[PDB]
Image (cartoon, rainbow, N blue to C red):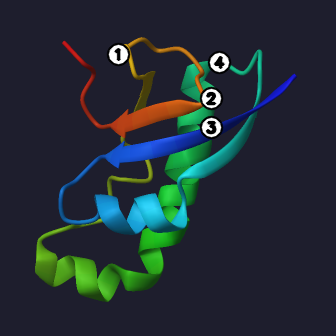
Amino acid sequence: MYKSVNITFELDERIDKVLNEKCSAYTVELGTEVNEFACVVADAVIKTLQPVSELLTPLGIDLDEWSMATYYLFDESGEFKLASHMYCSFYPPD
C-alpha cells in the first residue's frame, strides 16, 4: 500500500537542481489522490526554498504565491497517475 516516488522538478530552471537534490523523495499510499500528493510536494518545496529567499529575490523569484500555486504531478507518459518516477511542473502537459 506504500510506493516510493522520486520527482524530477520542472518548476523553474533557476532552482530545479536544488529541489532535485533536497526534496525529491516521497512515500505515497496507493489510493492518495494526485491533487493531495501535489500539495505534499508543494509544502516540501516551500520549506526547502524559504530559507534561501534572500538568494531567490535577486534571482527574480518571489515565493509569495508559490505556497498557494497549483503544482501538477505526472508520470513518464504525461498522465496524472502515481508512479515510482514523476515530474512536477506549474503547467499541465497540453
Residue at the outermost bottom position: 54
Task: Say which label, 4 or 3, has the lower sequence index.
Answer: 3
Vertical order, 22 against 7 (above or below): below
Identify the residue at horizontal 13%, vertical 83% (top origin). 58
- Residue at 24% x, 18% y: name it: 93
- For marks 1 and 4 on the same chain, the one whose residue lies earlier in the sequence: 4
Tell me which numbered mark, 2 or 1, is placed earlier along the sequence.
2
How far from the left and from the top, in percent, is residue 12? 22, 53
Give the quadrant of the C terminus: top left
The residue at 40%/45% (across/down) is 8
Residue that badge 3 annotates:
5
| Circle nearer the N terminus (2, 3) | 3
Residue type, label 2: Glu
Q: Amino acid at mark 4?
A: Glu
Tell me where residue 74 appears, x and y as whole percent. 43, 23
| Residue of label 2 | 36
Q: What residue is pinned by disc 4?
A: 33
At mark 2, the secondary structure is: helix
How far is mark 2 from mark 1, CA to CA? 18 Å
Residue holding disc 1? 78
